[PDB]
Amino acid sequence: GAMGIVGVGIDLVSIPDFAEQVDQPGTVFAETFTPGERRDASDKSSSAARHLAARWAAKEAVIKAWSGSRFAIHRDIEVVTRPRVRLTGAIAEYLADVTIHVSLTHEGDTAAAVAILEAP
Amino acid sequence: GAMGIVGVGIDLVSIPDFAEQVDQPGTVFAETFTPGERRDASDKSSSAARHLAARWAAKEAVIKAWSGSRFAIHRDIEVVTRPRVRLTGAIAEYLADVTIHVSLTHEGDTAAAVAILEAP
Amino acid sequence: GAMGIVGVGIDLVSIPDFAEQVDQPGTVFAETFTPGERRDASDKSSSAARHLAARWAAKEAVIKAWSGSRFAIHRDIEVVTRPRVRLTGAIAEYLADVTIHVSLTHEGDTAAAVAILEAP
């Protein structure tokens, strides 16, 4: 239907840098991934590191699209795999009527994502 | 005019990895690029490898935008260079009334593309 | 409101390659960044190189979105940091009624940006 763009976001993630940083106590990483997921992903050459990085890139792209938007709580945004966005608590309510498009990708050393927010 | 977004896609392509893989018989590569194009591109430091990778990234971004869309045959989608999309057979008909925006880029080791599908 | 997409652009920038090239007299770089900014950014491991590259990637993404558009003077487009677009002279007038969405990112060796042009 008739829609307007509300926000845009792009994010790049070095997978090797991600693997080094992900397993740290008390971080936003720790609030986002389980201890087991983070240990696994701690091995930069793993498939687990590859995917977790892409999920993190997507979440970041979505945050950028929103933060630059007229809506202004990171544990309220979850990205599941195609990439799906699930929202909770406060933000869920903010964007109840906003359509979220996200796409992710990974190649060798790098993961990337783009997010576009849309509303009538 | 008044439009809604139908799908989004992003894709990253390691050019060196592309050059190694592209020249393989019986692959989707073989259905997409001519034997000559694929041999040329087999040299990772070439300009031919650079461009073929960007064309492949674009095609992939477009596929992602569509696959995640309400439309659900890869030799029916062709990308020509600015990036242009030409469709044939089945998919041509599916997206007869869908507007396709694609953009590509290459820098050193990496090619990238984004695609956005749009419809009233 | 009801909007249609007018153009799309993506751009990738090797930061090390940027640092080598940026400080060159009489170039588009020289028309875009001050001598001081360009000398600073000449050090590839600097934070100044990181940000200038991201600004350059954004400007390029915006140029791509426009060049592929029905509007057809690079010192008329400026990108300021979130990324903001400021236009002058000719192009300012062209896009007076066009909405510009831009997003940028940097990770290690690479900067990236995407731009989307929109109009009723």
Image: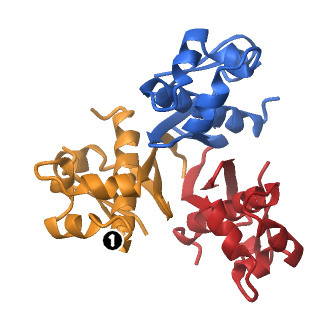
Chain colours: A red, B blue, C orange
Q: Residues within 10 Å of mark 1 (few under 14, many from 20)?
A: some
The image shows residue C57, relative to residue A61, as above or below, that is above
The residue type indicated by label 1 comes to: Ala
Q: In the displayed structure, does residue B14 sit left or right of residue B105?
A: right
Residue C6 in sight from this viewpoint: no
Q: Residue at 68% x, 23% y: name it.
A: B95
When the figure is inspected, residue A117 is found, relative to residue C71, above or below; the finding is below
Q: Label 1: chain?
A: C
- C26 sits left or right of C91 in the view: left
Q: Residue at x 58, y 78 (%)?
A: A72
Q: Secondary structure at mark 1?
A: helix
Residue B47 percent coordinates (x, y): 42, 27
Left or right: residue B51 compared with residue A24: left
Image quadrant assignment for residue A91:
bottom right
Q: Nearer the viewer, residue A3 or A47?
A: A47
Q: Name which residue lies at 18% across and 43% down.
A: C73
Q: Nearer the viewer, residue B103 or A116?
A: B103
Residue corresponding to mark 1: C48
